Image (cartoon, coloured by chain):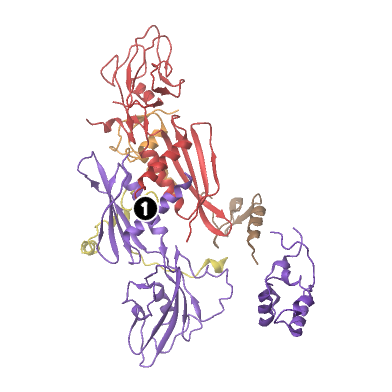
Chain colours: A red, B purple, C orange, D yellow, E brown
Amino acid sequence: TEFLKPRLVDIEQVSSTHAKVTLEPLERGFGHTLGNALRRILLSSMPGCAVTEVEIDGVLHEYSTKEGVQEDILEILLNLKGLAVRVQGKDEVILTLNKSGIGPVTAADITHDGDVEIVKPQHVICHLTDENASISMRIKVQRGRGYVPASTRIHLVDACYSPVERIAYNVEAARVEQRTDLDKLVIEMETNGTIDPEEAIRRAATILAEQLEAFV
Amino acid sequence: FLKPRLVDIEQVSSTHAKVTLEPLERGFGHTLGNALRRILLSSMPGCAVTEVEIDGVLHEYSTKEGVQEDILEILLNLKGLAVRVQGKDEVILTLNKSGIGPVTAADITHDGDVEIVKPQHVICHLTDENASISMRIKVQRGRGYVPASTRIHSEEDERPIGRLLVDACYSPVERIAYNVEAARVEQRTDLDKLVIEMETNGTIDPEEAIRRAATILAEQLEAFPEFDPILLRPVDDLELTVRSANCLKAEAIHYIGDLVQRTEVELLKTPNLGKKSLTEIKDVLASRGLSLGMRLENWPPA
Amino acid sequence: QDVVLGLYYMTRDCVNAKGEGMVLTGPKEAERLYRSGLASLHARVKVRIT
Amino acid sequence: EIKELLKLGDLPTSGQIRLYDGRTGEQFERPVTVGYMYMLKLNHLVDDKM
Amino acid sequence: REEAVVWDILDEVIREHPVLLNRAPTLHRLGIQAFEPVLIEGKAIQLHPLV
């Protein structure tokens, strides 16, 4: 009463931050359990650090207007949420936005630290309008083993930890020789660019394997 | 990154039990739980009865004199018989009984690996004083649902027409349900519990099932033209006499290719082949455009 | 029929729900908010779209 | 009388309960009607018609 | 004999070869529509919902 392992595996990836991997032969009903358990883990639980909270230099609140920037503070906060941060052994690091001028503040306009790595220099934080337009602020990162929104911090920025932006699994019929119907499991993911989707899947399901380490 | 493990396993009955898992992180009770439910329901070892040869019965659509049950009913009853074996993948049992009264599952002869979980289980009743039924109940082990209809492809002489094939019900699991309640361990922010309450026929232990389930689940993570076709036909396709076939097989001649290489000399030197047999072989070979002493040079390719 | 009831139940709003009034960078994390059970499928929300 | 016989059965008046997808394990939004319907198999069986 | 190979051969001949589907009360020309065959285990014809 031996079992079935998948023998045709192909990863067709678009660009870099996006990937569509497919697995041909899966026993009946294994495609849904695999696809789903991995989707749940991928989305709801993943290591990563982005932005938890950022202090406001001009005002004390998320609702206000900065001299030199037409973007609302919340808007800039969303932009900050879209910032890719990969840190080293340092658990919580803080950066600074020191810059001024007649043009937009990019992710390359942030302060460079030792353990901090920003994957996207073209990333837009906010614009800078005419003249000097005084602007600079301190940005604090944090870790999570899942997705924790700003409202969830009860005792503000939405903290997007899991690198996954989008996860979907499509299960279709798999034909192998004289075996009637099998599952074909297609996992399609989009990430924030910090960790590539390929390894991301591995480490994701690896958490699953760690969870089962006390049974098999 | 705390990994879960098991805790008290509460057996409320021979039928079903509730297995529990303590150290579960945020939301993992569901992710682990449902996935565990899936494998639990789907893939599990089972021993369900397959083949049954009864006394005077040619087909499942007859009625045996002395039993109020139709034969098909008796097969359907047998399919619901729960047994567990240890060292044997397939065992055959023998059922025997007579006189007026119900024939239960405890009326079978007990074997080494045979364990009857429901001795009270009713196979069929007996209506007359002198009326007796004997049967061979061939019980093999497998996974999933294997109907009787797909069972015949291989075929290979199931000729004992008295043998009625029955649909394979292989699976210990009846009902599986998983509930996550918040589980407070002494010191920890917030953790969850996993109460998997399962239903079985008693033929599988809860710890065993819960073990193999996650065993398989993790196990999936392991990845994330010349010559005549007629020369390779078995000698039985020549449709020789039983004697000639057995003699040839005894001389290491299992296929037509092996036979056409041999000469009359060599065949007559065998301990069991007379002139009649050789005449027969030459006749059947000539009838299909073949003969003895045929050379094909290159025996065999792969 | 089924499909249009699907898009109807999807695209629709109630008065109050999970994540009511919050803001998100785009559809990606909108769906990411929904699938994690944090945000209700139908809730009044401002999002940046292109 | 039906609801009154549902009370005696420990089951809700609505006749609707919570159901969970056997795939994702997650709950279905809104209660669904579950019950016991008597269903017949007419003889149009496909292996005849085909 | 339905030898195991022939199935694969069938998969070859089916690929780019369309088939015609038709229903009983044919009125407008859409009453008959061509599709691309997908091999199915069963005796029933699977028809796209939008059609």
Residue of label 1: B36
Q: Position of residue A37 (x, y in %)?
A: 39, 46
Which chain does the numbered disc 1 sit on? B
Number of numbered discs on residues:
1
Q: Classify A78 as above or below D50.
A: above
Q: Amino acid at mark 1?
A: Leu
- Compared to residue A211, the image places residue A50 above or below, namely above
Q: Residues within 10 Å of mark 1 (few under 14, many from 20)?
A: many
Residue B247: percent from left, percent from top: 68, 79
Q: Is residue B17 above or below residue C47?
A: below
Residue B273 located left or right of residue A165: right
- Quarter of the image with the N terminus of chain D is bottom left
Q: Nearer the viewer, residue B91 or A149?
A: B91
Percent x, y of residue B241: 68, 82
Q: Where residue B99 sits in the image (x, y, percent)?
A: 35, 90
B180, E25: nearer the viewer: B180
Q: Tell me the SS state at disc 1.
A: helix
Viewer-proximal residue among A28 and B19: B19
Quadrant of residue E2 within the rendered picture: bottom right
Residue A165: quarter of image = top left
Q: Quadrant of the C terminus of chain D?
A: bottom right
Q: Residue B289: name its quadrant.
A: bottom right
* Residue D47 as seen in the image, left or right of residue A115: right
Regarding residue A68, the answer to whether it shows in the image is yes
Q: Is residue B190 left or right of residue C24?
A: left
